[PDB]
Image (cartoon, rainbow over all chains, first blue to last red; front, side):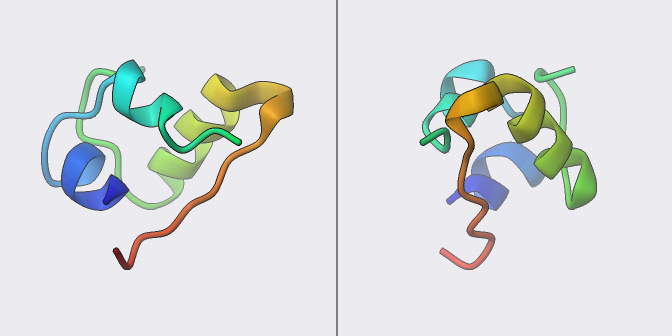
Length: 21
Length: 30
């Protein structure tokens, strides 16, 4: 989930936008 | 701001700025 993708590895806009409504 | 390790409030704030009026969901336990 978001922690694995953005906290323990380097985040990206692409992945952040997967969590927008 | 996006292209780094983002944890806790730092991640919430990034989601807030990126997602804007759409809002977002923050689910740290998946």
